[PDB]
Image 1 (cartoon, rainbow, N blue to C red):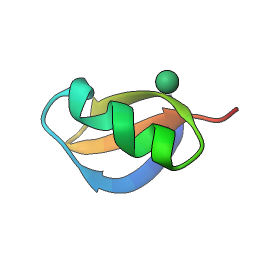
Image 2 (cartoon, rainbow, N blue to C red):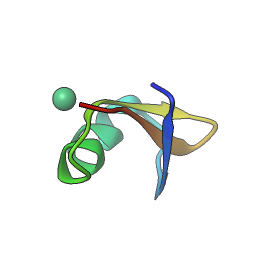
Image 3 (cartoon, helix red, strand yellow):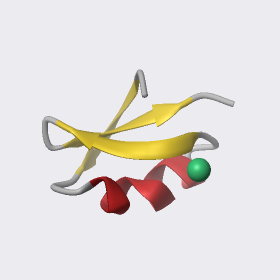
Image 4 (cartoon, protein in one colour):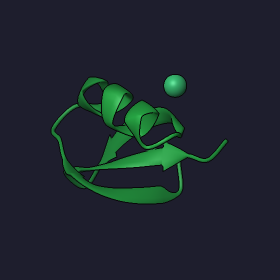
Length: 39
Ligand SMILES: [Cl-]
């Protein structure tokens, strides 16, 4: 998604919890950082 959070990753699975804990959804890893979809 299009919110970029300052959390590092190499796989989208690693972004599931960071995005949830940020109040957002559908964590994905893009260019080694997590992206989230706003509620
Ligand atoms: Cl989610």
